[PDB]
Image 1 (cartoon, rainbow over the protein chains, first blue to last red):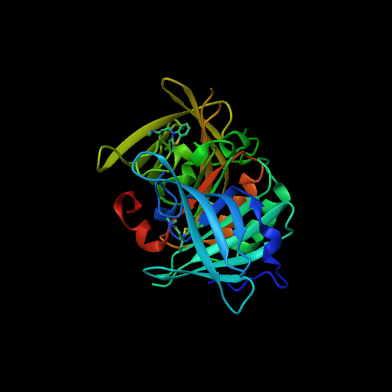
Image 2: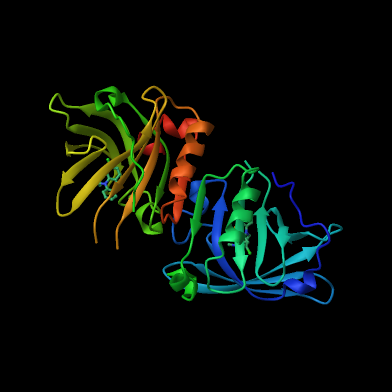
Length: 159
Length: 159
Ligand SMILES: CN(C)CCCN1c2ccccc2Sc2ccc(Cl)cc21
Ligand SMILES: CN(C)CCCN1c2ccccc2Sc2ccc(Cl)cc21
């Protein structure tokens, strides 16, 4: 369970282009296949004026790379947003420098499905951002991790 | 490319029961699906009197958990065995204490497919054996890692 958040977060400053450089999850089944439920590739983060967080992403669904937009609503905690659905889902922002890397996790309640990503601003392998990611995950019950190469990061659905 | 071998290896002492507690590989495609080519679950290591290494394992193939045996022949290097096939495949033993953990890698030539496992003697999560595994992998170009839980380790094909 995630007890690492970004103190002092300014969300407006996370807007723009992102790349899902690596991903990790609590169960193998969340990331194993091409259409696994947590295999989501972030494209853009779009904070709303009201301080909500629109997420633009790609997902492989029935043989193809589909585009999706979801909205995570603000909460009392600056680093935590809620996607109301069949479940209470939370987006947690763990850490960021705004200009290079952002670590975030998604979690529901059930047991608890948890997936986290290291997002970066450019199609480049950032070893320092990846160290910070592994550091964060040491405290979490993860059983699968994937990372993409720069070629893949320029393809839809990282193919 | 693997430049970590077990100095002083006595193979005869690796015989018996093993469990594939974690696995890592150079390409996502080698481990991603249930029937991915490197998704192999070790059952037993059986050194031959002549110093070859028989490997008993399970593999999910066309909807089912199949049993297989393969033979890796000795070489001039005690820690390196060869499986002659369509490719020159090597089994490399990186480290072991014989009684708890064994790290090993499999590699071919092409680019180079590489997969490594942390094997343990019991259906138990060995954090020290897993630290040694991550340490070993730091030097290798891995892009997917999986680890199993004790329930899974007692099921065929870790289902
Ligand atoms: C789009 N939908 C298939 C998944 C949305 C919810 N979602 C999520 C929620 C709870 C646990 C794990 C995940 S994976 C994930 C990765 C990226 C994003 Cl942006 C959202 C999620
Ligand atoms: C049985 N066959 C599907 C795979 C045999 C060769 N094999 C292998 C070789 C070169 C690169 C990667 C691998 S994965 C693997 C994992 C365990 C074992 Cl024991 C062997 C292998």
